[PDB]
Image (cartoon, coloured by chain):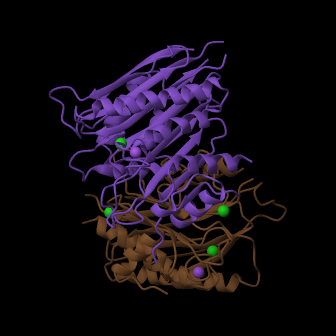
Chain colours: A purple, B brown
Amino acid sequence: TVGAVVVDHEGNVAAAVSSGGLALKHPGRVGQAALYGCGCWAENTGAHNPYSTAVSTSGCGEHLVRTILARECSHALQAEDAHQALLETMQNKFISSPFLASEDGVLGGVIVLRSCRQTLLVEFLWSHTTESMCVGYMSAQDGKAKTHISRLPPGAVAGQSVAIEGGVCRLGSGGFVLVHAGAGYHSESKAKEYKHVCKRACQKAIEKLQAGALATDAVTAALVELEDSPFTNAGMGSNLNLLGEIECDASIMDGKSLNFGAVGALSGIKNPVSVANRLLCEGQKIPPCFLVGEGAYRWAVDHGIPSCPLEHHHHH
Amino acid sequence: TVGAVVVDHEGNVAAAVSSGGLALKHPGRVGQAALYGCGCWAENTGAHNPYSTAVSTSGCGEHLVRTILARECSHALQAEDAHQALLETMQNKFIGVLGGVIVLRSCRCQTLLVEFLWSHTTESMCVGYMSAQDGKAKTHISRLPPGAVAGQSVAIEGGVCRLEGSGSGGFVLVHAGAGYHSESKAKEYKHVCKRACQKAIEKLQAGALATDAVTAALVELEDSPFTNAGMGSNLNLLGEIECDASIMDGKSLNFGAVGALSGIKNPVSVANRLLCEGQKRIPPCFLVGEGAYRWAVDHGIPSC
Ligand SMILES: [Cl-]
Ligand SMILES: [Cl-]
Ligand SMILES: [Cl-]
Ligand SMILES: [Cl-]
Ligand code: NA
Ligand code: NA
């Protein structure tokens, strides 16, 4: 699973998530990366909301769904202390959720940012209960993406302990991006590989922002790079399902409009996040926000999103 | 859309929802009746939840901004005044957007105090309800007041039911749709709600789980050609039926759901079967499309 969160120079936030789901899953199984409130969340400051907040999740899909973690994190981040709010959410609303009390271990990760105001104060954090999680972050002013394999400390137990880190950033046409390329066990073997795709994904988002793009288009450009890595379980290289076929989940949310787009069980499209973003975009102009399976493919093709008919399945 | 909520004689709750979705929708469009937290919710009392609560919602395709409706109603119903809490929630969310909800919350006092409500901003909503003690299902057509504008006002009514003895009883509240008022189809909506409640109670009285009872209710509601669910669902853009359904169990908190399901007579039966198998890698809780069809047939669920 891959994800990204973006804030532009005005405090407009966006979030997206893309995944290939569980290996050998039954055909048509849709997971967290497609589900409203679960895979990602983005919400600009407003009446109640003193902060703009963006969240993207990773790890065990079912664990993330049952606790609606992305939205839960965004609501907790309206509290004054962001570090403490996220840590308590991960401990109490995730690991200790009654919705997961049957589970022997709760496995998940999250990336967040929140901003508030002509200076923009961005706080960004990542937290995970998996052994590790690869992140990358970049601001348009620092102009050099930083990547980091966050690991659980010695003595921690994967699925029972929480790791959490983060930082702060004061920001024209700039902005800030944080991405992740998977939360689970890691191998030092392809650790530089995850770090490299995270760096490139940050650079693409930053370049989009520096060209005047909307937050949603910049977060989508980040996820396109993350998907395209043959090493990530999203887009190309997604785990194969029980029938040895590709079925992708992806979604995106805009903090300003609160509009949402999502695809589930999608095969034959190179970049699932692009269909999610096109659904969100076309929906701003009763438009659909969530398409699955055969109809999602046909809708993507009809809108000129690059396809792979040889990778598309349509069983009877 | 059709939905039902149930509480068994022990205070266990369940909820389910089933819909054909939006007429002429693009193929593969999945709506709220399939989405966790959105179409239905069921949660027994717990360390923060003083009431066992169950919620089923009905929408007219216009899904709401920053809204996970069934779960949000369940959380709001932890306040002391349930009527005010549902009213505030409907107002702060819908008021315009068209939709409706049925809810119940129970608590142990051994006796069970069950409060049940329905609320809509559509012109009308048909509901039915029944306790195992009384033995006669009651059906009713809820209307906006004279002079109200759909999407600019909220109707809300409900009742209170006391169950006791802890035999094999319970309570069920169903709805057959929130939408435009049809004087002509009113009798048919009331009759299917009647049959749905009776099936739900028959299950409870046989000792069944609350999820089996709420499934039996929705099977009846689905089968009516008048409901936009199962048989008679709105046809999509290509002239085909694609169904969404889900179900939640308040005791285990488990969940099952299908979206864009074609070719299966009773979608809620697949959602319930996904939940039941989950009770035993975590099994899938949400299947869509052809994979959902194949899974249903592979599990002996009748196709049409
Ligand atoms: Cl599976
Ligand atoms: Cl990955
Ligand atoms: Cl549509
Ligand atoms: Cl209906
Ligand atoms: Na990939
Ligand atoms: Na029907």
Identity of the residue furthest to the front in this view: A310
Q: Is residue A315 left or right of residue B3?
A: left
- Give residue B301's quadrant in the image: bottom left
Quadrant of ligand 5: it is: top left
The vertical placement of B78 against B39, above or below, is above
- Give residue A259's quadrant in the image: top right
- Give residue B180's quadrant in the image: bottom right
Q: At which x and y percent is residue A206?
A: 55, 25
Q: B297 or B4, which lies in front?
A: B297
Q: At which x and y percent is residue B250?
A: 38, 60
Identity of the residue furthest to the right in this view: B147
The vertical placement of B22 against A303, above or below, is below
Which residue is located at x 81 percent, y 60 percent? B148
Q: Is residue B23 left or right of residue A227?
A: right
The answer to whether any part of residue A51 appears in the image is no
Q: A191 or B152, which lies in front?
A: A191
Q: Is residue B114 left or right of residue A307?
A: left
Q: At which x and y percent is residue B98?
A: 70, 59
The answer to whether any part of residue A248 appears in the image is yes
Q: At which x and y percent is residue A175?
A: 58, 22
The vertical placement of B209 against A272, above or below, is below
